[PDB]
Image (cartoon, rainbow, N blue to C red):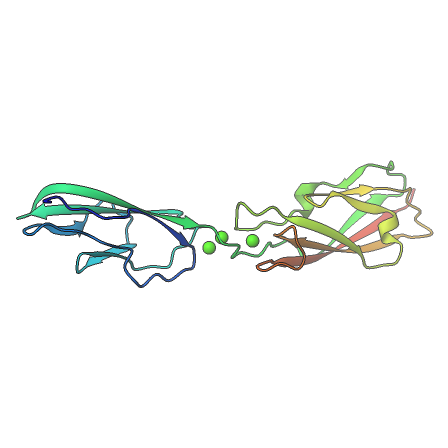
Amino acid sequence: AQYCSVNKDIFEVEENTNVTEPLVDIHVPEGQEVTLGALSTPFAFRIQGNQLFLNVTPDYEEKSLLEAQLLCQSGGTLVTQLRVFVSVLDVNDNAPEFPFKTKEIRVEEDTKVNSTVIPETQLQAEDRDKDDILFYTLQEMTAGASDYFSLVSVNRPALRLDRPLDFYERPNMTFWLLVRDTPGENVEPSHTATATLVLNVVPA
Ligand SMILES: [Ca+2]
Ligand SMILES: [Ca+2]
Ligand SMILES: [Ca+2]
């Protein structure tokens, strides 16, 4: 019983969790001392009273894996070394953001029905939760607008022309574009962003 040990060396910690309590007791044989080695993730861990602590609140978007190198020395010479891993778990802690608030697109009256008029690249939002699937909804602001345009799908926000345009009858169509980072509208956590789309019909 003359080797350093830990009973647990893989920890899962949700990002934004403050862990003040020890992760683990380090069993140190009489005559040895344990310190953090230089392969340890910088500014993450400390050892006090032969216990390993997290000093910081993890952020999955900054770093998803934290490593502690435990060096077990006797008179300053290395006897053994242990690794401890903290696997950081992603939380939905970022809101999707559109790169615009209100935006206008001009569309020729004779645009072919079923044409893409705004590609996904011009409408898509970005969410710093890289794994979040974004769900897009189009809501008419001016009555009848949804008769003319729709999104290709809730996850592919390309705007498609669905019916022939008529400059005289309806030269302006305005929409609310909503994005959320959850499939469900009423779940928690869920973040929503909104933008306005103005479709201006140009005549022949
Ligand atoms: Ca984060
Ligand atoms: Ca996150
Ligand atoms: Ca998110």
